[PDB]
Length: 113
Image (cartoon, rainbow, N blue to C red; front, side, top):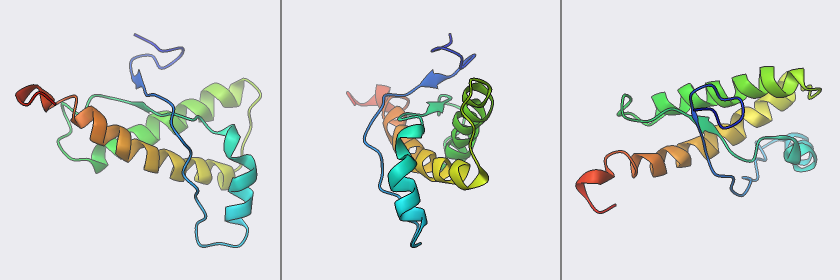
C-alpha cells in the first residue's frame, strides 16, 4: 500500500497548522510566511510495535521529513536547514497527536474506542 509514494506507511489526515514562534524574533515571522510549503499532514507506522509515544514520533518525524527531503526536493521543492527545522517542529507537534489517535485505533479494540 502506498498513498502516492510512501512505499508502506499510512498517510494521515490534514489538520490546522500549529503557530510555531520558537521564542525568536525572526523564526515566528519567517514561519508565518512560509508555513503553506509544508505537508499539512504526516506519514507514520502502526504503534503496534512501539508502546511508547516518542519512539513513534522520531520514527515518523523521520519518514515524513525524509520523504519531503527526497520526494518534494526532487520535484523542484528545495529548502534550507532553517526551513527543514520549521518542518521538524510542525511534524513533531502534528505526529504526537496522530500517535494519540492511532493509539486509540490500536489498543481501542478492548474498549468500544
